[PDB]
Image: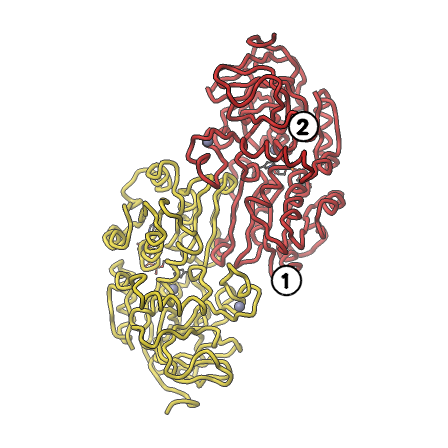
Chain colours: A red, B yellow
């Protein structure tokens, strides 16, 4: 009988860029029509949430960040049909309305109801469910998972297996699905191909998992932090290279290593220069390069379109190209059936109250995924 | 007999950039091992040849330009197995060695023996078969068709049907195949899709022919020269737009016209700005944009990689992605079988001696293809 009532609970509020989060009481309004209020159980720390703190991923502040999570439905608003109270759910930072031209397209996943392209930091109705110190607080990507309770639109939540371990499957809400799908769905990596993966964090490791699942013969991990190489090899990298070790640009190194360029490359960092390097290192006639990393806000890259004229394909994707609400429950079912592993991404576990310590671990280079438990 | 002897003949020599072609006597050496000497019958004037004159497509000078042609084999060197004297042939500006990693790849066509990436202006053996006034003259793309006779490597020639009309099928050597293949093979335009085509010259009109052949429902032609619109509609454009008629950037106009972005766009001009505009006007989640136009040498474009992160695909191709020696004879057979039309591309037919007048028709906006006859 919190149904229909304001919930007071602890959240991690970001009042200002480049500051620690503030763990303090917020008010969470009850769900309106076609909204769902969720008791959070676990949430991952994704680099994207750090990019909000840095101001390189722009969204209105003050904000409740967090987008990679799982929890249990506390209550549903009028007209909700796809979840019920007590269901295990993953919030969907890329919604799936099922009605727009993108949701109807066989390839498209970047649903037109998204709050990513022109971020408002609201619910679909352009309002906020969060108050803190009597002030309205923004949502983030329609999820806001750094809170003991959040409210999401129905098109931004999926029901998952009632027996799911939420402290693992939260990663299906961002890192795992994004990297894995970038390899298997967006690039469509082929058997016996040579792949290069720039960035060996939680998302790059999931790209290597996808490239190994698709049968790549060679998977070259690229990182300036050599501490990341051991885990990259554990999940399928065949060799790792640190650009800092070489006199020549790493695109020339990777072209040499692959006897004329790789089949597939992935940028999984968020830098303009590595997006161009990753395109250049794929074979000039038939290579494919996928951008996964989030670039610094409003900045343009410079490149020579002759890289494309010879035959390269350049593409990007959100959330591994997966239609979110269709895909997430299937990915959970596949995890439950041991079709892929999440433990290699989880390097640290902390209670929610130690969220700043978890951000310090990511910023130091020491962690892949820290899972926060409520 | 001419076999085994130097031929003295008329060619159009380009001694330096931004000068008219010089019609004069050249000496054409006999073919060496694995070379083919061709009597030219017809050659088209392609914008790429004008870009050599402008200095925006860099190749060593002085040069015999011309790459879109057909002729008859005069003689063969030792070891030639794929053509014989008397055969009708089309020179291949993109070769097909059949042995390199690209030629062996199911998608690749940019054969590693090409003279496009790092142009030397020679035969495969690094020498020239042309002299003029006692000076060696460079080849262009392994073809050099602005000459009564040329010598090509065997991997740069295809045998075609003995009954084909060379004054039309010369366009299968460049413009038609480039535009048609960019639509049907590189973009893989789908039935009922909406396409935008930037540039309505000979290659852009061939892109429209391919989009119509693939069953596109809407084909929007874009040109600053409204005199190009009537012929674009004859070969399948459903509507034409001139960016100069609008207050808003044309990417915004096309996104509005297509109710949120086109399925397929094509840049068929050669400008950095229209390459970015064409990418932007394709739907952000599932759009495909193909670069066909040749950009100005050594210039980089500037773009926001968020255009790709949402889901766009950006790709370019040489020669419509066709593997050149396999494809050109089949395209000629398909033309003989009335599967497509070439007459709509031909606006002017001039004697070879009128090459400069042909180029002035292209520069003035008055022609699509001028065919020069020997
Ligand atoms: N497209 C999408 O849907 C999603 C994109 N993102 C983005 O993916 C990127 C990766 O996220 P995570 O794996 O969580 O981050 P992470 O920070 O854990 O991993 C990035 C890795 O890149 C390495 N790196 C940094 N600079 C480098 C350089 N110059 N050259 C080579 N390696 C370098 C770092 O050492 C680190 O190991 C971030 O930009 C993030 O915002 C994350 C998930 C969703
Ligand atoms: N990728 C490949 O294998 C090939 C590429 N090319 C390139 O394709 C391009 C087109 O070649 P052609 O059709 O022979 O050229 P063309 O000059 O006949 O056609 C170009 C059209 O673009 C239009 N145009 C110029 N500026 C424009 C602007 N700012 N906005 C909109 N329209 C504009 C012109 O009015 C003209 O109708 C050239 O860059 C050529 O070098 C041609 C053939 C093979
Ligand atoms: Zn939708
Ligand atoms: Zn994320
Ligand atoms: Zn080859
Ligand atoms: Zn051409």
Give the label, 1 or 2, closer to the camera.
2
Tell me which numbered mark, 1 or 2, is placed earlier along the sequence: 2
Q: Ligand 4 shows up in which quadrant of the image?
A: top right
Q: Which residue is painted at 63% across and 28% down in the image?
A: A161
Q: As displayed, is residue B1 above or below residue A82?
A: below
Q: In x, y percent, where is residue B193?
A: 37, 45
Camera sees residue B326: yes
| SS of the residue under disc 1 | loop
Disc 1 target residue: A259
The part of the image, by quadrant, that contains residue B205 is: bottom left
| SS of the residue under disc 2 | loop
Query: Residue A164 bears which disc, if any?
Result: 2
Q: Nearer the viewer, residue A39 or B126?
A: A39
Query: Residue B40 bears which disc, if any?
Result: none
| Residue density around tag 2, few if under 14, some if 14–19, many if 20 or more, within 10 Å | some
Distance from label 1 to label 2 (Cα)?
44 Å
The part of the image, by quadrant, that contains residue B269 is: bottom left
Q: In x, y percent, where is residue A18?
A: 64, 27
Q: Nearer the viewer, residue B150 or B189?
A: B189
Looking at the figure, which quarter contains the N terminus of chain B? bottom left
Judge from the rendering whether residue A287 lies leftward or rightward of residue B178; answer left or right.
right
Q: In x, y percent, where is residue B48?
A: 38, 63
Q: Chain of mark 2?
A: A
| Residue density around tag 1, few if under 14, some if 14–19, many if 20 or more, within 10 Å | few
Q: As displayed, is residue B337 above or below residue A18?
A: below
Residue behind label 1 places its C-beta within 8 angstroms of ligand 5? no
Q: As displayed, is residue A31 above or below residue B176?
A: above
Q: In x, y percent, where is residue B43?
A: 33, 71
């Amino acid at each position: 009988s919190t149904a229909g009532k304001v919930i007071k609970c602890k959240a991690a509020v970001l009042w200002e860029e480049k500051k620690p989060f503030s763990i303090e009481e917020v008010e969470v309004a009850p769900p309106k029509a076609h909204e769902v209020r969720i008791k959070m159980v676990a949430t991952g720390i994704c680099r994207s949430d750090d990019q909000v703190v840095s101001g390189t991923l722009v969204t209105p502040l003050p904000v409740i960040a967090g987008h990679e999570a799982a929890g249990i439905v506390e209550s549903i608003g009028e007209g909700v049909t796809t979840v019920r109270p007590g269901d295990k759910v993953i919030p969907l930072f890329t919604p799936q309305c099922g009605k727009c031209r993108v949701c109807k397209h066989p390839e498209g996943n970047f649903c037109l109801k998204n709050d990513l392209s022109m971020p408002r930091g609201t619910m679909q109705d352009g309002t906020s469910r969060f108050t803190c110190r009597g002030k309205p607080i923004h949502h983030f990507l329609g999820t806001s998972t750094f809170s003991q309770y959040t409210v999401v639109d129905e098109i931004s939540v999926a029901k998952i297996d009632a027996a799911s371990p939420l402290e693992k499957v939260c990663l299906i809400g961002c890192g795992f699905s994004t990297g894995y799908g970038s390899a298997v769905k967006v690039a469509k990596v082929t058997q016996g191909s040579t792949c290069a993966v720039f960035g060996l964090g939680g998302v790059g490791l999931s790209v290597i998992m996808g490239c190994k699942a698709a049968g790549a013969a060679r998977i070259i991990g690229v990182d300036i932090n050599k501490d990341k190489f051991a885990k990259a090899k554990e999940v399928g990298a065949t060799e790792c290279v640190n650009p800092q070790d070489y006199k020549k640009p790493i695109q020339e190194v990777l072209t040499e290593m692959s006897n004329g360029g790789v089949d597939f490359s992935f940028e999984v960092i968020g830098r303009l220069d590595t997006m161009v390097t990753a395109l250049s290192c794929c074979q000039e006639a038939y290579g494919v390069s996928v951008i996964v990393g989030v670039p610094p806000d409003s900045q343009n890259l410079s490149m020579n379109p002759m890289l494309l004229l010879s035959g390269r394909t350049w593409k990007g994707a959100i959330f591994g190209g997966f239609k979110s609400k269709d895909s997430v429950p299937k990915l959970v079912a596949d995890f439950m059936a041991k079709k892929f592993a999440l433990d290699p991404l989880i390097t640290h576990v902390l209670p929610f109250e130690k969220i700043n310590e978890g951000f310090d671990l990511l910023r130091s280079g020491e962690s892949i995924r820290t899972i926060l438990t409520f």
